[PDB]
Image (spheres, rainbow, N blue to C red):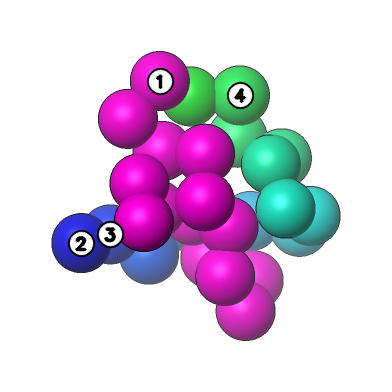
């Protein structure tokens, strides 16, 4: 999995990274 800095549920607009967690971004 991943954990890229995110703000909302989908503040990344990425392909393999749309599932944002606690201030994070991932695929699932």
Q: Is residue 6 above or below residue 17?
A: below
Q: CA distance from mark 3 to mark 4?
A: 15 Å
Q: CA distance from mark 1 to mark 3?
A: 13 Å
Q: Is residue 11 visible?
A: yes
Q: At x 32% / y 30%, what residue is drawn?
A: 16
User: Residue 23: where, in percent of width, then height?
Assistant: 64, 71
User: Residue 21: where, in percent of width, then height?
Assistant: 57, 70
7 left or right of 23?
right
Q: Which mark is residue 6?
A: none
The answer to whether the residues at label 2 and label 4 have Cβ atoms under 8 Å apart is no
The answer to whether the residues at label 1 and label 3 have Cβ atoms under 8 Å apart is no
Q: At x 40% / y 20%, what residue is drawn?
A: 15
Identify the residue under disc 1: 15
Q: Residues within 10 Å of mark 4 (few under 14, many from 20)?
A: few
- The quarter of the displayed image where residue 12 is located: top right
| Label 1 secondary element | loop
Q: Is residue 5 visible?
A: no
Q: Sequence-wise, which precedes: disc 1 or disc 2?
A: 2
Identify the residue under disc 4: 13
Task: Point out the stretch of residues depicted in magenta.
Answer: 15-28
Q: Is residue 4 above or below residue 24?
A: above
Q: Sequence-wise, which precedes: disc 3 or disc 4?
A: 3
Q: CA distance from mark 1 to mark 2?
A: 14 Å
């Amino acid at each position: 999995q991943l954990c890229l800095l995110c703000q909302t549920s989908r503040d990344c607009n990425y392909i393999i990274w749309t599932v944002c967690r606690d201030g994070c971004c991932n695929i699932s």
